[PDB]
Image (cartoon, rainbow over all chains, first blue to last red; front, side, top):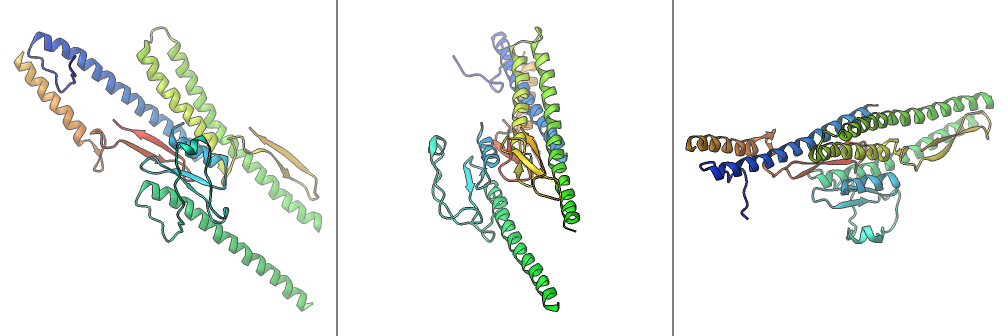
Length: 54
Length: 108
Length: 108
Length: 54
């Protein structure tokens, strides 16, 4: 196996492009998952703000 | 629990010591001189995994809020000083009240 | 005159007991909001359309909110007197001009 | 295919620019140097919540 990332994406060939669809999908799951962490953190801090104001 | 949750749990479970966490993720514990004499001894499994090192005397003069850890420890130190000042304000308040009763009595 | 003064102190005493009940209830207000949000997330996750990835994504906000409840319980206080973590237990509030007339407030 | 690869490298460098340059008043966030920062939300010390940016 070879470590691949979005930086290593090379779509100049059919094989490279197919590898790039999978790589980008994994990256999109990484971005979404972090965005869910930051969304949960924001909502939690809004609940905290309401509690502290009360 | 994460380390910052261990800190808030210890805060709610006692008032003799105040726990915190600094930038390096190290648990700081501050026993004010208005509540604890001598040295604090740490034991148990959690303290075994969080070797607490020795204690250093900190006062308001040595407050340094240029770090996350220093700022947290300075909130506790300023609280010990605030208790110290309030206590002496109450001793001077009692002294004034007792001296007002003394003045009334002497007038009679 | 002793009863009149003790009634003034009793009115202050009742008011303070109102303050602790008010602050504790206000904290429980956000515990209800956080719990209801966790219930909507639980219902959404139970849907068969969701796959493992989305169920984990919902679990992230469930854990964030659950830690939010524990923070409310451990940090809510009335001048440093923790209320919602169970260390308050039962405290009697003296509402009366003579001793022995107090009401037991229990915070869980 | 090469022309597309030039579009891929143009966007790939754009991602690295977003990571390196995104900041909140000069404090970079998405380049990995933010690491974990504790936000003090409470009337007394020790009440903090750690926000991790990746």
